[PDB]
Amino acid sequence: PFTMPKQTSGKYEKILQAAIEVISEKGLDKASISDIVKKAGTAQGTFYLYFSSKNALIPAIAENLLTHTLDQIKGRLHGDEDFWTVLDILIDETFLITERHKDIIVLCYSGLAIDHSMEKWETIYQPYYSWLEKIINKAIANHEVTEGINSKWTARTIINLVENTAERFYIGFEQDENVEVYKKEIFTFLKRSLGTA
Amino acid sequence: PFTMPKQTSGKYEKILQAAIEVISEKGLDKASISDIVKKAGTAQGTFYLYFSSKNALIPAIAENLLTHTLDQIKGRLHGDEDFWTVLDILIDETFLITERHKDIIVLCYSGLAIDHSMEKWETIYQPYYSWLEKIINKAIANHEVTEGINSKWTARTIINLVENTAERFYIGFEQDENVEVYKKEIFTFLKRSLGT
Image 1 (cartoon, rainbow over the protein chains, first blue to last red):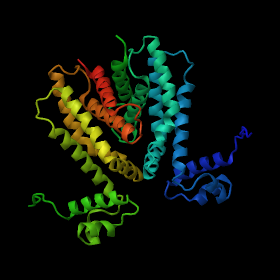
Image 2 (cartoon, chains in turn orange, red; image 1 turned 90 degrees about the vertical axis):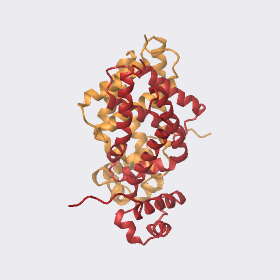
Image 3 (spheres, one colour; image 1 turned 180 degrees about the horizontal axis):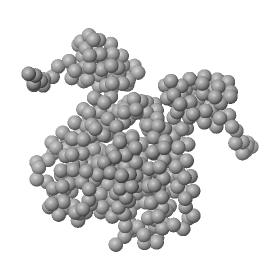
Image 4 (tube, each protein chain N blue to C red; image 1 turned 135 degrees about the vertical axis):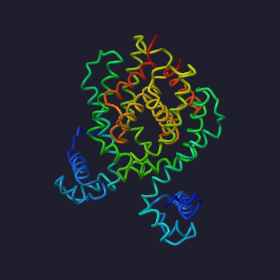
């Protein structure tokens, strides 16, 4: 039967990257599929082959930010780190990424919502949730994290908390203290709750 | 000189309530000012007096949901409750409101964001944050909550986590367990961390 080629195709990627650049330089609503397409060096047909509209770009943009976030975190790990060290890095990267790409995060909230698909964001996070889940199980087996907790739920809770804290600081502009104090606050809060005796 | 005459319900409230109703009917882009205005029993001029556009309605709608949320929680309290009892009620009400008004919550995320004003939401939550902060201070004094934590930060953290969990369940559709298990999960997570 049919076996999908390894095909690492370019056109789709060319347009998505182009769209990300145009939307950044002038905003989502002032962008033209025309400008995007001409910046990617293709015809309008190439755009519509992959996206029904400008809004349809949101889910794909959110997925790329998510895999970028996970890659960054993994990029700073070797695999044998203790749980708290992994957490430190996850917290640091999340604040760094939120600071630098807040425009994209706000864009995802607006789009996914406008199209009644905020649940797609959960699907998108699956690989990140799954990855943290295994790390928590590994931390439980090594007595770094209290036994009994629901690891699937906890992975998601940890990620929500950290991102909400980062968003409050860089997007909600709650900066009553140095950013390092906020990151330490999240860490201590999580430590007191998941840490073993 | 001037001292604002005391507040009363007028056109503003009429239009906002109408807008909320019209938007529940079809959902924004389908709702026209003519739609809303005719529903509130006024002319189009009354709409533009208070809102420059349909998007301008979002912040006001969000404040009303926040006020409704705080009112609900307070409605179930007498004032002498222990911290864990207040929390339990806060968790229950948040899930209840998210279940019932998820379309309003989604509408707020889409609008405030489209306008580059997600910070307005933090301003909007100020009365809720302050109220919780005061409750946490009282709980610290009564040795119900560990001493030393930052009350302002913890009040916001508590509210974030609870609302994210409720949103994951009703909006994200993460329902791998009965909703009561999720609510209990948040409570235990918070109790192990702030617990005495």
